Image (tube, grey):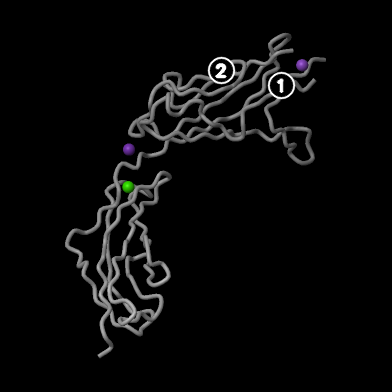
């Protein structure tokens, strides 16, 4: 008797001869174009094979219901195409059911799920507080001495608005904490060097991060 297709990979549910059902995965940034994004990468790659003729792939049903305005699945290659840029204010995700059927003979179809996440655009870079003191004094011959503190904010929502601090230079002489506090990492020496132009970097938590930088002028003071 004819057997139908199965989606890959087929990992058997233990103490059965049944494949565990698959949920394929994709993620698409909102507002980007078809031309930029196509073909959409699916993980793992969509594939079905005859358990024993040809194979036809389709999207059977899905939600939200206007998915056919946004996606096309090639019937022979399973390649997934975006048709229009998605706006995350209208769609945060799509959940699709896909099917594979035998071309010659009874369809004996297999089914899988396909989840497509829509990623929020990271519209803005962090913005340092404009009235921060940037001329900073610190005494020599002191390690772990507090130098000063910066702050930046980011308008975007979620991870896209969460600010992280790092130094752009002199990473052997200073350090910065998650709240923007800068300390010496070693004992400085005025006689050796009395001035540093230190770069602080503010980065957001986005998949595609944005960054800003601030210059601080550090003066090393005599112990007296
Ligand atoms: Ca941002
Ligand atoms: K958005
Ligand atoms: Na078959």
Mark 1 Cα-neighbour bin, 10 Å: few <14, some 14–19, many ≥20: many
Image point 30% across, 48% down: which residue?
125
For marks 1 and 2, the one nearer the N-term is: 1
Q: Is mark 1 within 8 Å of ligand 3?
A: yes
Residue beneath disc 1: 5
| Residue drawn at x 76%, y 41% as measured from the top left | 14
Left or right of residue 172, residue 109 in this image: right
Residue situated furthest front in the rendering? 192
Residue at screen point 42% across, 19% down:
69
Q: Secondary structure at mark 1?
A: strand
Q: Where 174 sits versus 66, above or below?
A: below
Quadrant in the rendering for residue 52: top right
Quote the CA–CA distance across marks 1 and 2: 17 Å
**In-front residue for pair 84/175:** 175
Give x and y (percent) for residue 186: 40, 78
Residue underneath mark 2: 74
């Amino acid at each position: 008797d004819d057997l139908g297709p199965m989606f890959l990979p087929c990992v058997l549910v233990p103490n059965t001869r049944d494949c565990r059902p698959l949920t394929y995965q994709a993620a698409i940034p909102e507002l980007r174009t078809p031309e930029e994004l196509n073909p959409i990468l699916v993980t793992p790659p969509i594939q079905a094979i005859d358990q024993d003729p040809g194979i036809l792939y389709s999207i059977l049903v899905g939600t939200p219901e206007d998915y056919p305005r946004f996606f096309h699945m090639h019937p022979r290659t399973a390649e997934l195409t975006l048709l229009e840029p998605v706006n995350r204010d209208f769609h945060q995700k799509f959940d699709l059911v896909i099917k594979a059927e035998q071309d010659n003979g009874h369809p004996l179809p297999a089914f899988a799920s396909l989840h497509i996440e829509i990623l929020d655009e990271n519209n803005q870079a962090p913005v340092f507080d404009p009235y921060l003191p940037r001329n900073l004094s610190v005494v020599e011959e002191e390690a772990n001495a507090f130098v000063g503190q910066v702050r930046a904010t980011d308008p975007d929502a979620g991870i896209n608005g969460q600010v992280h601090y790092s130094l752009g230079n002199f990473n052997n002489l200073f350090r910065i904490t998650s709240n923007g506090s800068i300390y010496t990492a070693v004992k400085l020496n005025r006689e050796a060097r009395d001035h540093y132009e230190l770069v602080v970097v503010a980065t957001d938590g986005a998949v595609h991060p944005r960054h800003s930088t601030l210059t601080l002028y550090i003066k090393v003071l005599d112990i007296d």
